[PDB]
């Protein structure tokens, strides 16, 4: 195939995405959840890891690592320590709200995913770390977990398969950095959410010091369907190495901001028009799009004309798919102010552990605030580029990179706007 | 078959202790926890 | 501020203890973690103290340290790292307005100013009656429903200056307004009609591969 | 048999498995710059001053925490490594106060000296600086926490060596502060050692305050008599007057610590 999109409802995974059908166990089973889970578990971890491998699934949390290979790090003999699956429901990336819909409207997909994914890793339990602001969603998930326990689908002898598995829910307390895998582990352990250096990797030393795999909610929630329908069925969607369906969030200056499931490698233009009702004021009114949440560099309208929404396509456009949270800005937007507010966000979210982000991001925030008013000289633009490069790749965790990249996208594509603002300020003063 | 009403309305009646009450309810379903061997890293 | 100074209202002798029922809830919290790692319960238990007490005096932090046998400083570290912990009293309704870019692009400013005018306070302040506290927050994870606010545990979405002033009017009257979007849709589906998931979902066994 | 071969700027060296990149550089007499790393404390990896290029690897690694792999070539003087050091030093100094004339660390300051050897020679920071309020932790250790670079050495020493968990970090991001949160005195028989391990003038000796500069002191290597341990010390004198007492490293006796009575 060479064209992508127009996913049919028969091939959509999250069929209760909009919560118009019963989200509890009875509705979930009627939609195909918890069907033949016992057979899947009895197939074995290597079979399950094979299907996730053949499916081409990649991490939906933002980094996009191949899921089958990543999960196989746990497929090793035990050494006396328990093994854990940690499901990342921190959902903190600005623009991203897909995981919220899964937890509250399709909770049993996530619960079954924990069991199937946990079985592949040989984990004894799953901890679902959900951000503390998602109180009503956590309670929904807690109700679904109780139904699964009462029905015998999880817990002792889960699904009558002779495999024990617990699913715990632990809430955050307000921290974007606790979405980072190792910071999430540190938070579960009762410490400040500060990322760990690697090595060790979590598959060797993770939560409570034990072998751990951290997986995104969407990554986990689709695994049971991949096992039932096959990895080949999943890989028949999207371009090579960009397999499967993807949940998108389209927000900002669109007519009907929404969440939707669509094929990977759908054209960005087609996604915005078919599902979000087009750019506010027409496509000609488009200024820039942030395609994968605040951490991904923006792209100008010219690039958005033909780009495809998948990992490889957006990398060649000098950005990334990220969480696939599309933030649309029309030509009435103050683009410098829009980006400056994201840097302010990263300033408020940096854990402060390591020097380049603790000091660099606060420094970038001060410079951007002046760039908004034009109270700077053009020589500071190349200075700000260099500062962002001193943060990128020098910090413990990827938040520092996530703050550097949006600044780089602004300078790459809107340098004339920044310079024009400094010229206007100078004549006014 | 209806597709025109919202079927996620239970959370309009959740309260301060809803989440922890459910956690207390689930306590009898869990497998026994593993042990590091000591009461804490400071023991 | 991230340093503490004792006052008559907030000092180690300020009364705090968990109610008998909250001690039962604490036991279930601590049983969720491997033995020898009780410190993992610090966040849920600290949040439990806030839910009972409304905020976290230094004496509440000290009690959590005692129950879990963790040094009090390690609890202070948690209380000051996570922004959902209130180390000063807050009003009965903690209004939290998202002002990050996706919500800002859809006019969260009009929501912020509407609240300030109606309550006659500035961001960060509490009303003289101590009913409302207003602050700005970062992305609350409901970006497609912008602009939006969180009041205590509830989200209010697709807001306009009229809608939020109606929510505040209901709160002042002892009524508890229903959460969710106020614009016409139910959650995150596009307004003007579903563009997907229109047909009834398939049932058990659909598309299942052979061998299972 | 156990040893593996790695290279430091092309020079072969044999190291036990688990040896860090920084330790492998010691073996050939190269001292990687550091702030947070102390060989008697647990590894932290937060200052990032020890970033070093590994040949053929696109990303610099934290030498103090990264275990060295077989066949790695550690480029301790490459352009990538030098630019990494300059960038980190630039961030460390962005909010640091212009205190050297009034700061007791001046003249024996690891921030000053590694800035001289590995940092740039000028500033491009055009904003205003952070200013942080001071903490009283007793009559022995003066705090000027605007000088603190958040290396967490004092926190790790207190928890691990002194066995006192009173020091920590409060807040987040650029506002992260080291202290006790509450008003508490750090009175331990080993407390004065945090003065030595603090790389900057954030923690300084109260009795010693303002009396001398390091270059003008004569160092007499002696022994402590305040107990029967026999701690090795250095007696700093100037113009015939004892100015202060410092630990002298002896692995088999006091390592590099002394008690507050000795100090
Ligand atoms: C600052 C920061 C925030 C992150 N937030 C999330 C998040 O909210 N949800 C998530 O799944 N991954 C988040 N991640 C990515 C995780 O670190 C990790 O890559 C992911 O949980 C792995 O799961 P996956 O392979 O299924 O995507 C974040 C990373 C960073 C650096
Ligand atoms: S990059 Fe920022 S968030 Fe990540 S560890 Fe360093 S200071 Fe913390
Ligand atoms: S700590 Fe060092 S660099 Fe900072 S003021 Fe003192 S002498 Fe100068
Ligand atoms: S006070 Fe000194 S030792 Fe402690 S964190 Fe700050 S710079 Fe490091
Ligand atoms: S930007 Fe406001 S909820 Fe995400
Ligand atoms: S000395 Fe290695 S990061 Fe600080
Ligand atoms: K010092």
Image: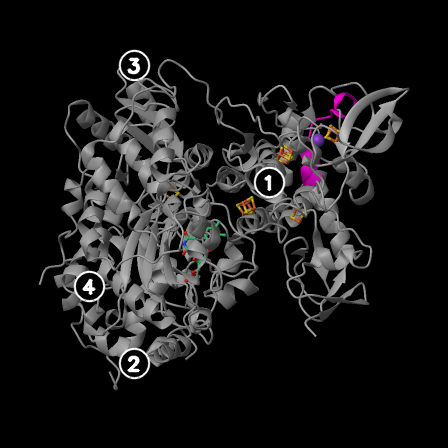
Task: Determine whether label 1 and label 2 are within 8 Å by CB.
Answer: no
* C-alpha span from label 1 to label 4: 65 Å
Out of D114 and A319, give the one closest to the viewer: D114
Residue D216 position within the rendered picture, expressed as x and y whole percent measured from the top left: 88, 26
Query: Hey, which residue is sitting farthest left in the picture?
Result: B1
* C-alpha span from label 3 to label 1: 50 Å
The residue depicted at 25 percent of the width and 25 percent of the height is: C92
Q: Is mark 4 within 8 Å of ligand 5?
A: no
Give the chain of mark 4.
C
Regarding mark 4 in the picture, which secondary structure is present there?
A: loop
Q: Quadrant of the C terminus of chain A?
A: top right
Q: Quadrant of ligand 5?
A: top left
Residue A308 position within the rendered picture, expressed as x and y whole percent measured from the top left: 46, 66
Q: Quadrant of the N terminus of chain A?
A: bottom left
3 or 4: tag closer to the N-terminus: 3
The residue depicted at 80 percent of the width and 32 percent of the height is: D234
Image: C185 above or below A359: below
Residue D107 position within the rendered picture, expressed as x and y whole percent measured from the top left: 82, 30
- Camera sees residue D228: yes
The residue that label 3 is drawn on is C128
Q: Which residues are magenta?
A: D90-103
Asked whether the residues under marks 1 and 4 belong to the same chain, the reply is no
The residue that label 2 is drawn on is A43
- Residue depth check, mark 3 versus mark 1: number of the one nearer the observer: 1
Residue C181 position within the rendered picture, expressed as x and y whole percent measured from the top left: 24, 42
Query: Hey, which residue is sitting farthest bottom in the picture?
Result: C211
* C-alpha span from label 1 to label 2: 51 Å
């Amino acid at each position: 195939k060479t064209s992508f999109g127009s996913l049919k409802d028969e091939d959509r995974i999250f069929t209760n995405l909009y919560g118009r059908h019963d989200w509890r166990l009875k509705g979930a089973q009627s939609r195909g959840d918890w069907y033949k889970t016992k057979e899947i578990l009895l197939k074995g971890p290597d079979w399950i890891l094979g299907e996730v491998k053949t499916s081409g699934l990649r991490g939906r949390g933002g980094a996009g690592f191949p899921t089958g290979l990543k999960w196989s790090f746990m497929n090793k003999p035990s050494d006396g320590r328990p093994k854990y699956l940690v499901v990342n429901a921190d959902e903190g990336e600005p623009g991203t709200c897909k995981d919220r819909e899964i937890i509250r409207h399709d909770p049993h997909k996530l619960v079954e995913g924990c069991l199937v994914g946990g079985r592949a890793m040989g984990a004894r339990a799953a901890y679902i770390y959900i951000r503390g602001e998602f109180y009503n969603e956590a309670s929904n998930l807690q109700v679904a977990i109780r139904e699964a326990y009462e029905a015998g689908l999880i817990g002792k002898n889960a699904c009558g398969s002779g495999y024990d598995f617990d699913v715990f829910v632990v809430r955050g307390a307000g921290a974007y950095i606790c979405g980072e895998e190792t910071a999430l582990i540190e938070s579960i352990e009762g410490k400040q959410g500060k990322p760990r250096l690697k090595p060790p990797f979590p598959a060797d030393v993770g939560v409570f010091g034990c072998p751990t795999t951290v997986a995104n909610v969407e990554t986990v929630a689709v695994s049971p369907t991949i096992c039932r329908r096959g990895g080949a069925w999943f890989a028949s969607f999207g371009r090579e190495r960009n397999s499967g369906t993807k949940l998108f969030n389209i927000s900002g200056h669109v007519n009907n901001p929404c969440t939707v499931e669509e094929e990977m490698s759908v054209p960005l233009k087609e996604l915005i028009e078919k599902h979000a009702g087009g750019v506010t004021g027409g496509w000609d009114n488009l200024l820039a799009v942030i395609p994968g949440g605040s951490s991904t560099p923006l792209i100008p309208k010219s690039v958005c004309e033909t780009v495809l929404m998948d990992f490889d396509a957006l990398i060649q456009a000098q950005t990334g798919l990220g969480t696939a949270a599309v933030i649309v800005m029309d030509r009435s937007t103050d683009i410098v102010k829009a980006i400056a507010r994201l840097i302010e966000f990263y300033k408020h979210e940096s854990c402060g552990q390591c020097t380049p982000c603790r000091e660099g991001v606060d420094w970038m925030n001060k410079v951007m605030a002046r760039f908004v008013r034009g109270d700077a000289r053009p020589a500071e633009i190349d200075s700000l580029w260099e500062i962002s490069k001193q943060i990128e790749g020098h910090t413990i965790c990827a938040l520092g990179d996530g703050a550097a990249w949006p600044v780089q996208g602004l300078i790459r594509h809107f340098r004339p706007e920044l310079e024009e603002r400094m010229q206007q300020f100078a004549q006014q003063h | 078959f209806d597709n025109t009403t919202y079927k996620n309305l239970q959370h309009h009646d959740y309260s301060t202790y809803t989440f922890l009450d459910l956690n207390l309810d689930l306590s009898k379903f869990r497998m026994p926890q593993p042990s590091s061997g000591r009461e804490s890293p400071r023991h | 501020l991230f340093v503490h100074r004792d006052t008559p209202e907030n000092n180690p002798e300020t009364p705090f203890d968990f109610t008998p029922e909250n001690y039962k809830r604490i036991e279930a919290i601590v049983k969720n973690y491997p033995e020898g790692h009780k410190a993992a319960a610090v966040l849920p238990v600290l949040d439990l103290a806030q839910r009972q007490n409304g905020w976290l005096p230094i004496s509440a932090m000290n009690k959590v340290a005692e129950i879990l046998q963790v040094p009090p400083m390690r609890v202070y570290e948690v209380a000051t790292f996570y922004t959902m912990y209130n180390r000063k009293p807050v009003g009965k309704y903690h209004i939290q307005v998202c002002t990050t870019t996706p919500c800002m692009l859809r006019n969260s400013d009009s929501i912020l100013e509407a609240i300030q005018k109606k309550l006659g306070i500035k961001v960060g302040e509490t009303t003289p009656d101590k009913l409302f506290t207003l602050i700005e927050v970062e992305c609350l994870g409901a970006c497609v429903n912008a602009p939006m606010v969180q009041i205590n545990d509830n989200y209010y979405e697709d807001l306009t200056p009229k809608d939020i002033e109606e929510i505040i009017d209901e709160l002042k009257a002892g009524k508890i307004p229903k959460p969710g979007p106020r614009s016409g849709r139910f959650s995150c589906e596009p307004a003007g009609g579903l563009t997907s998931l229109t047909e009834p979902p398939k049932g058990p066994g659909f598309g299942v591969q052979a061998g299972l | 048999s156990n040893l593996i071969e790695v290279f430091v700027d092309g020079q072969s060296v044999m190291v036990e498995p688990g040896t860090t990149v920084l330790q492998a550089c010691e073996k050939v007499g190269m001292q990687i710059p550091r702030f947070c790393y102390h060989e008697r404390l647990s590894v932290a990896g937060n200052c990032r001053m020890c970033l070093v290029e590994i040949e053929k690897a696109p990303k610099v690694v934290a030498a103090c925490a990264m275990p060295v792999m077989k066949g790695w070539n550690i480029l301790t003087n490459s352009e990538k490594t030098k630019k990494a050091r300059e960038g980190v030093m630039e961030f460390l100094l962005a909010n640091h106060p212009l205190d050297c004339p009034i700061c007791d660390q001046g003249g024996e300051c690891d921030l000053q000296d590694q800035s001289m050897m590995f940092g740039s020679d000028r500033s491009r920071f055009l904003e205003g600086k952070r200013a942080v309020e001071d903490k009283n932790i007793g009559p022995l250790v003066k705090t000027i926490m605007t000088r603190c670079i958040q290396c967490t050495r004092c926190i790790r020493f207190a928890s691990e060596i002194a066995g006192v968990d009173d020091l920590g970090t409060t807040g987040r991001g650029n506002d992260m502060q080291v202290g006790t949160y509450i008003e508490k005195m750090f009175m331990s028989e080993l407390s004065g050692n945090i003065i030595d391990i603090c790389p900057v003038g954030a923690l300084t000796s109260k009795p010693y305050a303002f009396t001398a500069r390091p270059w003008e002191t004569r160092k007499t290597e002696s022994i402590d008599v305040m107990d029967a341990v026999g701690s090795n010390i250095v007696v700093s004198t100037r113009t015939g007057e004892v100015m202060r007492i410092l630990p002298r490293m002896h692995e088999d006796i006091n390592e590099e610590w002394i008690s507050d009575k000795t100090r």
